[PDB]
Image (cartoon, rainbow, N blue to C red):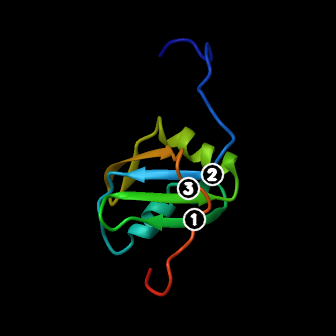
Amino acid sequence: GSSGSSGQKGRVETRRVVHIMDFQRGKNLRYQLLQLVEPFGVISNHLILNKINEAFIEMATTEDAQAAVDYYTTTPALVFGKPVRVHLSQKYKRIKSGPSSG
């Protein structure tokens, strides 16, 4: 509906981290969250929170992270057949795993 273009979204070239929220859990959860950004570019790193339904996935480029969120802000993102939220993090930087089990 309505005319094309007629405006532009606010964007920044700082950071490369896709924030994902509101997900259902299961044995393939790491994979399900990666598949929201795997077709969009090169995965650099990932982090899945235990205490709350939050996850952070760092792309090798800002354009790779921006392309995933530009699609998933309008298109419904899903995990385990249930809806989720997909945005860029203004907090997160270079992701790194904890020692042993982490």
Rendering coords of residue 38 (x, y %) = 58, 60
Alpha carbon of mark 2 to alpha carbon of mark 3: how far? 11 Å
Res. 14 image quadrant: top right
Q: Is mark 1 on a helix, strand or loop?
A: loop
What residue sits 57% from the left and 70% below the top?
96
Q: Marks 3 and 2: in contact by CB < 8 Å?
A: no
Q: Which amino acid does label 1 sit on?
A: Ile
**Viewer-side label of 1, 2:** 1
The numbered dot on residue 84 is none
The disc label shown at residue 16, or none: 2
Q: Nearer the viewer, residue 68 or 47?
A: 47
User: In the visual, does 101 lie left or right of 25?
Assistant: right
Real-space Cα distance between discs 1 and 3? 16 Å
* Residues at marks 1 and 2, CA–CA distance in whole angstroms: 10 Å
Number of residues whose C-alpha sits closer than 10 Å to that of mark 3, classed few (under 14), some (14–19) or many (20 or more): many
Which is more N-terminal, label 3 or label 2? Answer: 2
Residue drawn at the location 61% of the way across and 16% of the way down: 7
Q: Name the residue under label 3.
A: 37
